[PDB]
Image (tube, helix red, strand yellow):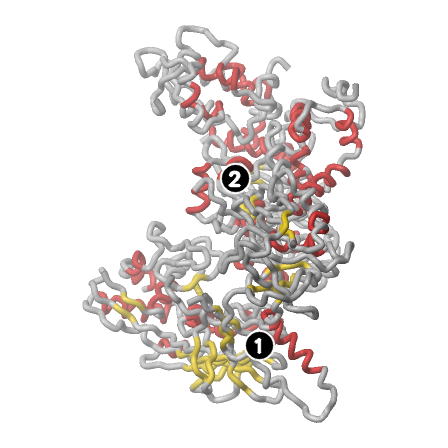
Amino acid sequence: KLPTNLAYERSIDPSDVCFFVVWPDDRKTPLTYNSRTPHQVDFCHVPYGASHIECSFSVSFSSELRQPYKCNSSKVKQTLVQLVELYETKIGWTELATRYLMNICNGKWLWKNTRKAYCWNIVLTPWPWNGEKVGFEDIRTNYTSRQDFKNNKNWSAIVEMIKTAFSSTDGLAIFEVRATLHLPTNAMVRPSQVFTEKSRVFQSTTIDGERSPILGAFKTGAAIATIDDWYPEATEPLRVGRFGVHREDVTCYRHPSTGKDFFSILQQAEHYIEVLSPAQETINDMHFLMANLIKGGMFQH
Amino acid sequence: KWYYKTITFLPELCNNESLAAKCLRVLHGFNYQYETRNIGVSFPLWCDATVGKKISFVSKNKIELDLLLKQHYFVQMEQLQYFHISNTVLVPEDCTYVSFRRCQSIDKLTAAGLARKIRRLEKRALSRGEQFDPSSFAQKEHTAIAHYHSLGESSKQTNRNFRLNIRMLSEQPREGNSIFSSYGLSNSENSFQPVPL
Amino acid sequence: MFLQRPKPYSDESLESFFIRVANKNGYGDVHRFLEATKRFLQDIDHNGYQTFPTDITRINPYSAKNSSSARTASFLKLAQLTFNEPPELLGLAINRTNMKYSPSTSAVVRGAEVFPRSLLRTHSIPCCPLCLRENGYASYLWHFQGYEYCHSHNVPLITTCSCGKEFDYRVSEAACTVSNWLAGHESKPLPNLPKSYRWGLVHWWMGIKDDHFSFVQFFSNWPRSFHSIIEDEVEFNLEHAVVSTSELRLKDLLGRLFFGSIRLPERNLQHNIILGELLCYLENRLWQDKGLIANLKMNALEATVMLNCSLDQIASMVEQRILKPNDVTDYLFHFGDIFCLWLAEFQSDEFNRSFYVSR
Amino acid sequence: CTVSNWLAGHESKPLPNLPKSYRWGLVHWWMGIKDSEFDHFSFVQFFSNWPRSFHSIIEDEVEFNLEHAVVSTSELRLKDLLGRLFFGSIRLPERNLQHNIILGELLCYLENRLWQDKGLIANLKMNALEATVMLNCSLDQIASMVEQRILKPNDVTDYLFHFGDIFCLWLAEFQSDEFNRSFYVSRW
């Protein structure tokens, strides 16, 4: 098992985020910050007189989880091809597609910029699509649980077209996303920060000539992937990794002494063909196994 | 013929801002009961990073400096020996020579302070004509601020955590025959009065 | 803000407290207010909102490995600035503790009272209507409390009880004395010991037996039962000595009775009279023969359960020549000398000698 | 004559009545604070204005070492905010605070005064061995709290923990049937 060369490619493709300042006269400018001074400290705020703040990125749902990228062995080839093909039938792509979509819908990718906000609205723009712009208005007081989304006019088609994008070979689904944040006057905005191996240096880009912060493309890929609450006695959803690492406290769950990490389940691949040919925990760890093949990564020793 | 009251700031675990303010807040209660204008700033061990221990008190009428010194703070901090009284000595007339002045420019640089500013410029242009926008008001990218050793202070009347900003200027051998104010100054309405340290 | 009129009374397991504030003002289940609480925890001046739960269960503050210290801090401001007249909220929380028993069962504190083990049912429990609601269910033995013949498993149609499916766990004579004993009454045949010792000794009868009619036969002759069970088990395991014929070591002479009744859970001699009466029959007969009770082999590891040490005072006692050497893991010392220095230098006010016979 | 006739167990005067094993701890608490012999005249006077003049001396002493604090308003140990009030009323002889209500009202002040003045009480810095003194544990049990993450930090002697963190810790992990906090819910 694990024959020294195995790797997958990712299946979710988020981009950078861009901050624009809309004026009352329907004019949009890029949100620019200030620097203060080696030792350098940055400061960003909403300019006075502005209505609200806009954000736009894009994400794609492709099908690179059906076969690996390099495989080195035709016994780990047809085994992992059969697992993703049997999970499509007995379980279905419903429980994963709903969890990834809600973190796009409820503004989870706005990390700490929603605290002290009056109202924010999020508009999707799917493709391929015959119909209308999809809306999610006043999300704090209208959309809070899995059921408020299921009452929507356009939830049956956007849980769909991701389910086909994982099931059909050479599939594709692309979402444009836009959000408007009604923040109070002179409110602070929190973008991503440059690493600077040992403060608060912003990750910037050039939009229309002047510099503007981004809040990252690996930063917004972490927010969508927080769907993991199958580690034992789970209280909070974590980001999908091989050893269940939590960031705020520097512990990690999912440790190999427990027997619940990825490399002690991936070795057990032949065991799970038998049951799927059971709804207690043999399901609740394939949701962790499928969310690792959608993640990517080199799997080799 | 000035005096000086050298203090000693000993106990090795102590803040340099909260104790230089509270020894000045007990000076701030003064000049609201005995309204004088004569007591200065005079840090002997000012340095660049992490200002040191000693502060002093300088005046020419030079008997209120002991009247200020017994005002329910050294009579309240006496036994657990944080500080001690100096020897009340005439200042020798050849020494180093600095000046302490409130800058107050730094306070109107922070992003809340510039929104505090362009709010005021909105209303005082009530003589009409143009219809201006707040779009053409910005701080650009670059303000290089080295060091100013801020001193935080709570307001007397209300609950505001305001702050002071005073730096070093050492020249000009003749201004200010003891024309200080409530906090001790070299900027406002009188002179740029230097200090003999 | 301003949850109108917190009403309630005592004797509740905290789960209907959120249900009683759910049935007011018109609200579905508890997912809304339960999100609006954790939204208010996500609101101003708070740091631990991420682990406050989501479902019908798990409001319990021992259900997480490490959000126990976060759940009580969550429950701190969940009573003060959200209620007019902040009620008795804190103390209702069924927490966990550091205590154990002698058969190595996890102790669990409600407000002052200890259940035998944190295992009991946790699911598929009976329930009776026309209260709001109970404290004592989801446990082993708490059935009726005065009104009987109420099991109420819902094989017939939906919505028999009129609450609205919030708590409502239902899917599609010697028992009355012990039920009044565990709920709290006078109970004249029973010696009126508190509920930490009530549930503390139900498992002590469950541990030695491995049964309500078999329960009360040990309590109908309570000044005779413990004295009779100690005299017929002491004649057992006497011909099976290990050294030659006598001077029997540890674990073979009363290794089950003495290691099963100590600190269950609190070391009080006023109420837990088991500890005083086992000390009576073992030490009303101090020197019977040469090597019968006192002259035996004992270890210092099983001596700190009475001496209240943490293997740090032994390095200052045996070198000061109180306990004479006749070493951590050997059966070295004797029971008569260790117990007497306990009585001479390790007493207390409630864990002491002046509570058992003579009364 | 007053402090004589409620020592042998006589339950008749409005001086407070304890199981009189605990009463000698109340006698020993009076000598530790005053740093003198066991006074009798002010001992009657202090319990005649009970519990009204108790919380005033608590308030006047936490005002004392905070007005005359040496370091700052933050980054402080619990010394010089509770210096002699906390370390001098722990074990007399046991923390069963229904009996010794000098800890039942001290830990009442520690409950109702946590999160005011921007967390002025919740940023008192503690070391590891104060949990062994207060919460009745050992140094090896603190290391079990760190490895399984129940206590969250931010060596024995170094000052690393926090006050609102540790007050809600012992209501969840370190609460025994004798050492409860519910014993004074009808006193405040």
Residue C206, x across and y down, in percent: 50, 32
| Residue holding disc 2 | D131
Q: Which residue extends farthest bottom? A: B129
Q: Nearer the viewer, mark 2 or mark 1?
A: 1
Between D68 and B2, which is closer to the camera in this rendering? B2
Marks 2 and 1 belong to one chain? no
Q: Which residue extends farthest left? A: A73
Residue A264, x across and y down, in percent: 30, 56
Gap between marks 2 and 1 measured at Cα: 46 Å
**Residue type, numbered disc 2:** Ala
Q: Residues within 10 Å of mark 1 (few under 14, many from 20)?
A: many
Between D117 and C18, which is closer to the camera in this rendering? D117
| Residue holding disc 1 | A46
Residue C286, x across and y down, in percent: 48, 9
Between D137 and C91, which is closer to the camera in this rendering? D137
Quadrant showing the C terminus of chain A = bottom left
**Residue type, numbered disc 1:** Val
Disc number for residue C138: none
Quadrant showing the N terminus of chain A = bottom left
C87 left or right, relative to C111? right
